[PDB]
Length: 118
Length: 120
Image (cartoon, rainbow over all chains, first blue to last red; front, side, top):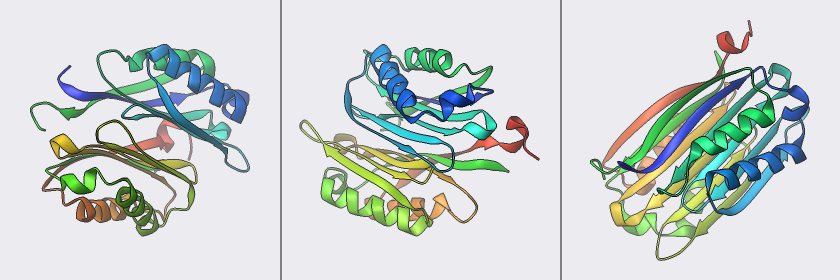
Protein backbone atom coordinates (compact mmCIF):
# COMPACT_ATOMS: atom_id res chain seq x y z
CA UNK A 1 0.00 0.00 0.00
CA UNK A 2 1.35 3.29 -1.23
CA UNK A 3 -2.05 4.91 -1.65
CA UNK A 4 -5.51 5.16 -0.15
CA UNK A 5 -6.93 2.95 -2.88
CA UNK A 6 -6.35 0.78 -5.90
CA UNK A 7 -8.47 1.33 -9.04
CA UNK A 8 -8.75 -1.05 -11.98
CA UNK A 9 -10.06 0.51 -15.20
CA UNK A 10 -11.03 -2.44 -17.37
CA UNK A 11 -12.14 -2.85 -20.97
CA UNK A 12 -13.94 -6.16 -21.55
CA UNK A 13 -14.34 -7.23 -25.19
CA UNK A 14 -16.18 -10.03 -27.00
CA UNK A 15 -18.37 -10.83 -23.96
CA UNK A 16 -21.53 -12.97 -23.86
CA UNK A 17 -24.08 -10.46 -25.20
CA UNK A 18 -27.00 -12.13 -23.51
CA UNK A 19 -25.30 -11.73 -20.16
CA UNK A 20 -24.43 -8.10 -20.98
CA UNK A 21 -28.14 -7.35 -21.55
CA UNK A 22 -29.39 -9.19 -18.44
CA UNK A 23 -29.93 -6.57 -15.74
CA UNK A 24 -30.67 -9.10 -12.97
CA UNK A 25 -27.72 -11.32 -13.70
CA UNK A 26 -25.29 -8.42 -14.01
CA UNK A 27 -26.42 -7.16 -10.64
CA UNK A 28 -26.01 -10.57 -9.08
CA UNK A 29 -22.52 -11.05 -10.58
CA UNK A 30 -21.41 -7.61 -9.45
CA UNK A 31 -22.48 -8.30 -5.89
CA UNK A 32 -20.61 -11.62 -5.99
CA UNK A 33 -17.60 -9.82 -7.41
CA UNK A 34 -17.73 -7.48 -4.45
CA UNK A 35 -17.96 -10.43 -2.07
CA UNK A 36 -14.95 -12.11 -3.70
CA UNK A 37 -12.83 -8.94 -3.26
CA UNK A 38 -13.50 -8.76 0.51
CA UNK A 39 -15.46 -5.52 0.19
CA UNK A 40 -18.51 -4.49 2.11
CA UNK A 41 -21.49 -3.26 0.06
CA UNK A 42 -23.18 -0.08 1.19
CA UNK A 43 -25.68 0.21 -1.63
CA UNK A 44 -26.13 -0.92 -5.24
CA UNK A 45 -28.18 0.40 -8.11
CA UNK A 46 -28.66 -1.13 -11.54
CA UNK A 47 -30.59 0.14 -14.56
CA UNK A 48 -31.61 -1.16 -18.04
CA UNK A 49 -30.61 1.25 -20.74
CA UNK A 50 -33.00 1.04 -23.70
CA UNK A 51 -32.97 -0.52 -26.09
CA UNK A 52 -30.00 -2.57 -24.85
CA UNK A 53 -27.46 -2.16 -22.12
CA UNK A 54 -27.04 -2.42 -18.39
CA UNK A 55 -25.48 0.17 -16.00
CA UNK A 56 -24.74 -0.37 -12.37
CA UNK A 57 -22.86 0.91 -9.41
CA UNK A 58 -21.95 -0.93 -6.23
CA UNK A 59 -20.94 1.54 -3.48
CA UNK A 60 -18.48 0.03 -1.02
CA UNK A 61 -16.92 1.43 2.20
CA UNK A 62 -15.00 4.35 0.67
CA UNK A 63 -15.21 3.75 -3.10
CA UNK A 64 -17.06 1.80 -5.81
CA UNK A 65 -17.43 -0.96 -8.39
CA UNK A 66 -19.14 -0.02 -11.68
CA UNK A 67 -20.16 -1.64 -14.95
CA UNK A 68 -21.66 -0.19 -18.12
CA UNK A 69 -22.49 -2.61 -20.94
CA UNK A 70 -22.97 -2.32 -24.71
CA UNK A 71 -24.51 -5.67 -25.66
CA UNK A 72 -24.59 -4.73 -29.33
CA UNK A 73 -20.81 -4.50 -29.31
CA UNK A 74 -19.97 -7.21 -26.86
CA UNK A 75 -18.28 -4.59 -24.73
CA UNK A 76 -18.31 -3.68 -21.03
CA UNK A 77 -16.63 -0.78 -19.22
CA UNK A 78 -15.74 -1.97 -15.72
CA UNK A 79 -14.20 -0.03 -12.81
CA UNK A 80 -13.05 -1.67 -9.60
CA UNK A 81 -11.91 0.94 -7.03
CA UNK A 82 -11.15 -0.53 -3.60
CA UNK A 83 -9.50 0.82 -0.45
CA UNK A 84 -7.68 -1.02 2.26
CA UNK A 85 -5.25 -3.91 2.57
CA UNK A 86 -8.17 -6.26 3.17
CA UNK A 87 -9.73 -5.79 -0.21
CA UNK A 88 -8.47 -7.10 -3.51
CA UNK A 89 -9.98 -5.66 -6.66
CA UNK A 90 -8.33 -8.35 -8.84
CA UNK A 91 -10.64 -10.92 -7.20
CA UNK A 92 -13.62 -8.93 -8.50
CA UNK A 93 -11.95 -8.73 -11.91
CA UNK A 94 -11.52 -12.47 -12.10
CA UNK A 95 -15.15 -13.16 -11.14
CA UNK A 96 -16.47 -10.73 -13.74
CA UNK A 97 -14.14 -12.01 -16.44
CA UNK A 98 -15.60 -15.47 -15.94
CA UNK A 99 -19.21 -14.27 -15.49
CA UNK A 100 -19.17 -12.19 -18.70
CA UNK A 101 -17.07 -14.64 -20.77
CA UNK A 102 -14.89 -11.84 -22.15
CA UNK A 103 -12.47 -13.08 -24.81
CA UNK A 104 -10.15 -10.08 -24.51
CA UNK A 105 -9.49 -7.69 -21.63
CA UNK A 106 -7.36 -4.63 -21.04
CA UNK A 107 -6.83 -3.45 -17.44
CA UNK A 108 -4.89 -0.51 -16.03
CA UNK A 109 -4.27 -0.23 -12.26
CA UNK A 110 -4.24 3.30 -10.89
CA UNK A 111 -3.26 4.42 -7.42
CA UNK A 112 -5.91 6.75 -5.89
CA UNK A 113 -4.63 9.02 -3.12
CA UNK A 114 -0.93 8.29 -3.21
CA UNK A 115 0.58 8.73 0.23
CA UNK A 116 3.39 10.90 -1.19
CA UNK A 117 0.79 13.29 -2.68
CA UNK A 118 -1.83 13.71 0.08
CA UNK B 1 -13.83 7.91 -31.49
CA UNK B 2 -14.96 5.99 -28.44
CA UNK B 3 -18.21 5.21 -26.69
CA UNK B 4 -17.27 7.35 -23.70
CA UNK B 5 -14.76 9.68 -22.16
CA UNK B 6 -13.64 9.15 -18.60
CA UNK B 7 -11.74 11.55 -16.37
CA UNK B 8 -9.97 9.91 -13.44
CA UNK B 9 -9.18 12.86 -11.20
CA UNK B 10 -7.19 13.46 -8.05
CA UNK B 11 -8.19 16.69 -6.26
CA UNK B 12 -5.77 17.95 -3.62
CA UNK B 13 -5.84 20.61 -0.94
CA UNK B 14 -9.61 21.02 -1.12
CA UNK B 15 -11.83 22.82 1.36
CA UNK B 16 -12.07 20.22 4.08
CA UNK B 17 -15.40 21.45 5.37
CA UNK B 18 -16.89 21.02 1.89
CA UNK B 19 -15.40 17.53 1.63
CA UNK B 20 -17.26 16.51 4.77
CA UNK B 21 -20.63 18.08 3.88
CA UNK B 22 -22.87 15.45 2.36
CA UNK B 23 -25.71 17.83 1.46
CA UNK B 24 -23.34 20.21 -0.31
CA UNK B 25 -21.46 17.45 -2.12
CA UNK B 26 -24.78 16.07 -3.43
CA UNK B 27 -25.83 19.55 -4.63
CA UNK B 28 -22.48 20.20 -6.30
CA UNK B 29 -22.33 16.83 -7.95
CA UNK B 30 -25.82 17.24 -9.36
CA UNK B 31 -24.79 20.73 -10.57
CA UNK B 32 -21.72 19.19 -12.20
CA UNK B 33 -23.92 16.70 -14.07
CA UNK B 34 -26.13 19.59 -15.26
CA UNK B 35 -23.04 21.53 -16.47
CA UNK B 36 -21.88 18.55 -18.43
CA UNK B 37 -25.20 18.16 -20.21
CA UNK B 38 -25.77 14.66 -18.82
CA UNK B 39 -29.12 13.18 -17.93
CA UNK B 40 -29.35 11.95 -14.32
CA UNK B 41 -30.74 8.47 -13.78
CA UNK B 42 -30.24 8.23 -10.03
CA UNK B 43 -28.11 9.78 -7.29
CA UNK B 44 -26.97 8.38 -3.97
CA UNK B 45 -24.84 10.09 -1.32
CA UNK B 46 -23.50 8.61 1.93
CA UNK B 47 -21.53 10.04 4.88
CA UNK B 48 -20.34 7.38 7.18
CA UNK B 49 -18.20 6.88 10.26
CA UNK B 50 -16.28 9.84 11.59
CA UNK B 51 -16.05 11.73 8.26
CA UNK B 52 -15.87 11.29 4.51
CA UNK B 53 -18.50 11.39 1.79
CA UNK B 54 -19.17 8.98 -1.06
CA UNK B 55 -21.50 9.97 -3.86
CA UNK B 56 -22.59 8.61 -7.20
CA UNK B 57 -24.65 10.27 -9.91
CA UNK B 58 -25.62 7.51 -12.37
CA UNK B 59 -26.14 9.13 -15.78
CA UNK B 60 -27.60 7.64 -18.96
CA UNK B 61 -25.06 4.85 -19.56
CA UNK B 62 -22.21 5.83 -17.20
CA UNK B 63 -21.43 7.66 -13.96
CA UNK B 64 -20.02 10.60 -12.02
CA UNK B 65 -18.52 9.63 -8.59
CA UNK B 66 -16.79 11.26 -5.67
CA UNK B 67 -15.13 9.81 -2.60
CA UNK B 68 -13.68 12.27 -0.09
CA UNK B 69 -11.01 12.10 2.62
CA UNK B 70 -11.53 15.34 4.59
CA UNK B 71 -8.59 14.56 6.87
CA UNK B 72 -6.30 14.76 3.88
CA UNK B 73 -8.02 17.49 1.81
CA UNK B 74 -8.28 14.88 -0.99
CA UNK B 75 -11.11 13.75 -3.21
CA UNK B 76 -11.18 10.92 -5.77
CA UNK B 77 -13.39 12.01 -8.63
CA UNK B 78 -14.45 10.01 -11.68
CA UNK B 79 -16.36 11.65 -14.56
CA UNK B 80 -17.40 9.08 -17.19
CA UNK B 81 -19.69 10.44 -19.89
CA UNK B 82 -20.93 9.03 -23.23
CA UNK B 83 -21.98 10.73 -26.38
CA UNK B 84 -20.90 13.80 -28.14
CA UNK B 85 -22.88 16.48 -26.48
CA UNK B 86 -21.92 15.58 -22.92
CA UNK B 87 -18.67 17.17 -21.79
CA UNK B 88 -17.05 15.75 -18.63
CA UNK B 89 -14.67 18.75 -18.51
CA UNK B 90 -17.60 21.02 -17.59
CA UNK B 91 -18.28 18.77 -14.60
CA UNK B 92 -14.60 18.94 -13.73
CA UNK B 93 -14.66 22.73 -13.83
CA UNK B 94 -17.66 22.95 -11.60
CA UNK B 95 -16.25 20.60 -9.02
CA UNK B 96 -12.79 22.19 -9.06
CA UNK B 97 -14.49 25.47 -8.17
CA UNK B 98 -16.89 24.01 -5.61
CA UNK B 99 -14.22 22.02 -3.74
CA UNK B 100 -11.57 24.73 -3.96
CA UNK B 101 -8.91 22.25 -5.10
CA UNK B 102 -5.46 23.83 -5.33
CA UNK B 103 -3.86 21.01 -7.30
CA UNK B 104 -5.30 18.36 -9.62
CA UNK B 105 -4.13 15.36 -11.58
CA UNK B 106 -6.43 14.02 -14.33
CA UNK B 107 -6.18 11.04 -16.67
CA UNK B 108 -8.59 10.99 -19.59
CA UNK B 109 -9.44 7.50 -20.80
CA UNK B 110 -11.29 6.60 -23.99
CA UNK B 111 -13.75 3.92 -22.92
CA UNK B 112 -14.86 1.66 -25.74
CA UNK B 113 -12.58 2.89 -28.51
CA UNK B 114 -14.14 2.29 -31.90
CA UNK B 115 -10.94 0.75 -33.26
CA UNK B 116 -10.80 -1.71 -30.35
CA UNK B 117 -14.32 -2.80 -30.47
CA UNK B 118 -14.39 -2.96 -34.26
CA UNK B 119 -16.68 0.00 -35.06
CA UNK B 120 -16.21 2.07 -38.20
